[PDB]
Length: 52
Length: 52
Length: 454
Image (cartoon, rainbow over all chains, first blue to last red; front, side):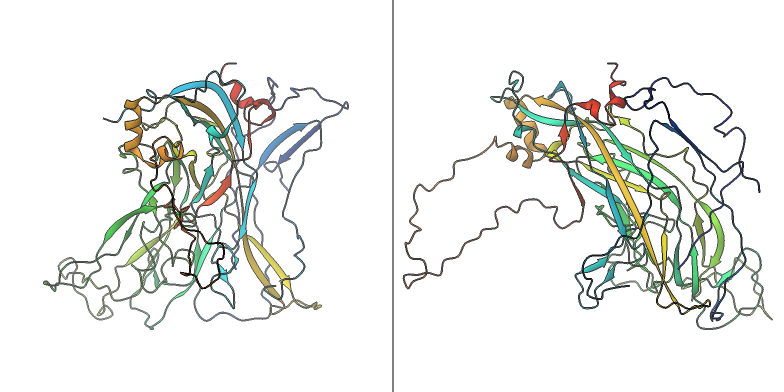
């Protein structure tokens, strides 16, 4: 009954996702940027900035 | 290195630590986005004593 | 003089999405547990992250459609056949790599830092160990099931010479059945029959035949209808160094080394083996969740699906987590070790999308010879070359059947048995009931219609 331990590797600044804009040209669904109910949901997950 | 015999004891828990997996993702929607996992779903009416 | 498949067909301009349901696969990663009373009833199957998950779709007959616009499908001379023009294989589990482990592996010594003379004797030194695997990804698509070889046993020779007892060697070409294990970094051979002590590879290989897809013969097939399109990417590198334990049957010559004595009176083994280990697995170098457009296949059969079925095979080793469950039998206020029983499980999912295009095939007399010599079964199903069976009237009737005017009449001919594929196990996925035409209600045609320039 084994279990391994995951560790991951170095974290750079070239391989980041944040602090830079995006432009929604054409979304993947059908409602291309329209939001109803006057709200929308953003969720982010970050591990690289989790110093304890 | 792991040789015979085993090193027996009624408890062998340790005080360890480990790192995690590096991960980043972003997500936009006009609805709370869904997610999944494996949960304990109940059996059929009888297994007739097959396996715990 | 095989001609290509774009001279005797004629592409139409009408497109058809299809789409599978979400498939799952739950079982044990190590061994297929059987019944305590039965040897043919499985309880939990052996599914792992190291197998050739081979899909076999089944397309519906295009001639079993009824169109109102009967101006293009002229059934005097022409017939219909699909073509593949796209594909997408998705996954839905996180990126995670799994380990396998033998409990009696032949790790005799350690041969990278210190193997200090003399020997430590003892007539058993096997033990429990575990390691990572050669990580890989590939996919093949074709109208015939893929071919793959493996090294194996054979008749050695005749019985004149008596030089040294050594096993013979011969590779074997066969068909890649599902459930078989990929090569994993210990050579593309049988391990059941060519090894004996079953204690050199981990437990998921020790009764298996690690085949490998013949990229060379399947490329050089004369019709070219086993490989539409193929991708691959893999890496591995060594982790440690060990060595086996036994009488090395082939002697090491005294020429190559200075003879020694004292503490060095008994020469050691020269039978090493390394251990593979896949490095970091990213999500940048993935090979799934991306479309693939076949603008021109590599073979002659330019995407056209004879036989109304495809064979898609795919294997991944990056998504090979092992869920470990832990349960108890009693409730005790202190920690114990005899109070718990634990279990290993592995889950697996897939998804297929397709986009097909049907094209009509004219049938001259010149053409119907050419299709006849490729395979005769394809002309049988369209029912174009047939004969009248003879024998106008029989007399095989009686009003009473269970009597004494009887010859003990027998029936049930085995006539519907024609496919030679039932000796092999495929994963069947049904596509006969899920075609559609309005692309835009589906998660791929919107990624397709921008590609067409419309």
